[PDB]
Length: 35
Image 1 (tube, one colour):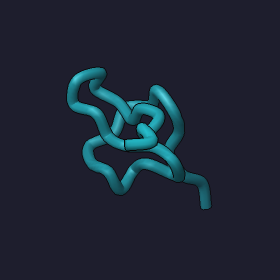
Image 2 (cartoon, rainbow, N blue to C red):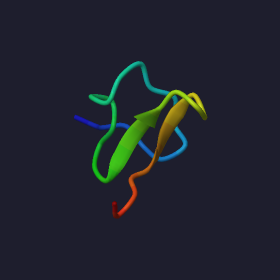
Image 3 (cartoon, rainbow, N blue to C red):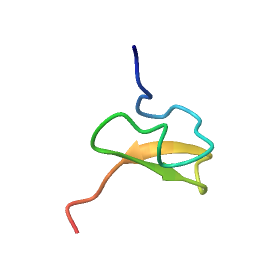
Image 4 (cartoon, rainbow, N blue to C red):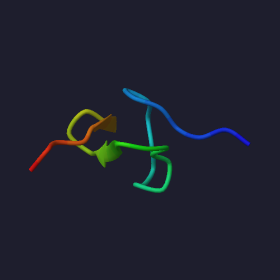
């Protein structure tokens, strides 16, 4: 199976594949921060 992606819309943080986080600000998963 496949997973989410960067700059890809998501309804939750579960859609995020890896190193990604659902950001309601951009309406899609964004590259997680170091902090």
